[PDB]
Amino acid sequence: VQDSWRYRIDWKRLAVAGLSGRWLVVVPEDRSAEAAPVLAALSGAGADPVQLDVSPLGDRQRLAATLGEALAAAGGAVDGVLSLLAWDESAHPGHPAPFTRGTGATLTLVQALEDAGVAAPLWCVTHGAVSVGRADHVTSPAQAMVWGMGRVAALEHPERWGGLIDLPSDADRAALDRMTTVLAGGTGEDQVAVRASGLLARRLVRASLGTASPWWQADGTVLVTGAEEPAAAEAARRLARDGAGHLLLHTTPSGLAGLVAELADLGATATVVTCDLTDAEAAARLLAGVSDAHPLSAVLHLPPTVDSEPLAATDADALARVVTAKATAALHLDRLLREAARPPVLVLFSSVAAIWGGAGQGAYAAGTAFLDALAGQHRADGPTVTSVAWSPWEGSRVTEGATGERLRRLGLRPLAPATALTALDTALGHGDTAVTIADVDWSSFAPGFTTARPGTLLADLPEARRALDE
View 1 (cartoon, one colour):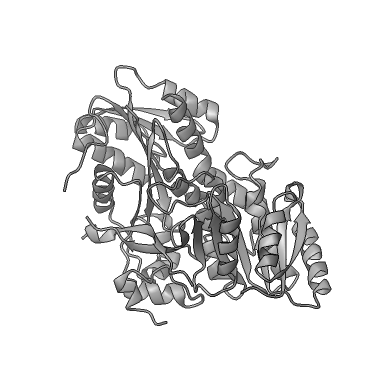
View 2 (cartoon, one colour):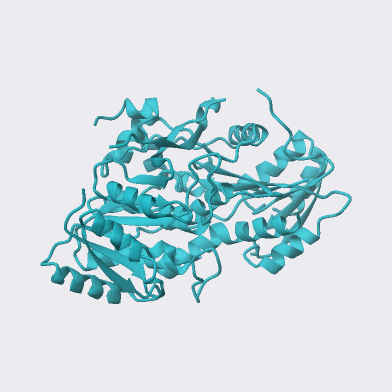
């Protein structure tokens, strides 16, 4: 139907239950201070930890030399690799926020490990990157981009990917002790949160549903971005049909007159504006232009599609560019709307690439995971952010039969635009903050997803688990 298209991410509490050999701990250079208690925990856990301070700006070849040297020193083998690189939240010189030096550096490390021939599993540790539930806010949406790319690294380099572990936003000694139980490989899990309560593991489950509430006001203006694209046009047609009186349509610098005349027939007065929403000044201009007789009621943010590459084949600047196209405008919209604080609703269009990952989608998953993380941050006054992670819509490029036929054979059926927009309305109307909408035949998907890499993300979803074995 489409009520069977709703999924969400849940964090399953794990039952209460050592480490050995050489562990390389990769720390960003000017961050040596922290790590001290990281090596103490690993040592105390019974590992022999070696710190490897790197320049996050550094070349892949420099890092591979550094790793090969460290691997030569251990006799040619090491038991694991623990990256603290995500902790580097500093700005990168070539690139706007939210891309950080830690984002680039982590990618560089995945590549450089293979250049140095380190066969040991890589574990990437974040803090404040995921929300396990109600009271647990995301404090570093930028570190969630490592989770997005990391799930993709798991599928692309399954023999050398250990996992992802998120420490409490601040993170104390009892938390680093539980970290070491995860590194020991006893949990069977590879996407783990460490909380005051114990360990939690990531699961995609059904989010099935009768009291809606309005998420836009007829007298307010609703902004739709990337309106030159078919998804965004249909959304605006739907809002007019449903009774929205005022539409502001943004288009990405090179639809237009036809669409405006059409929406007037459907009942809305729409105006069209063009500017680079990755430029905060222009985003600020856009918002200030909304009439005070019709204040901003809701924003539908549809960032441009981007091209993907395997992780081995991309580089830190390409990754950074894709993060910018998917996430920087949303960063600014969230900030300026926060700074103007009824909360408008800010609806981000994310992607199943950020939820479960796909080979070739590394960069796309990083940027789109930043959207899903914005939705998990506390906002004292608004805007109320919803991130919806979509599977591809009919007509869209990836449904092209080449890669399109691949998706279909993995059991992903392109979404009809009408049905998808009704699913969007049900979610916003039901108060959803983070939901996945996707039409998935799990009997094809779950075997195709686990063919190279075992995992447990779908363990608690019946149609998928029944298509699997332990």
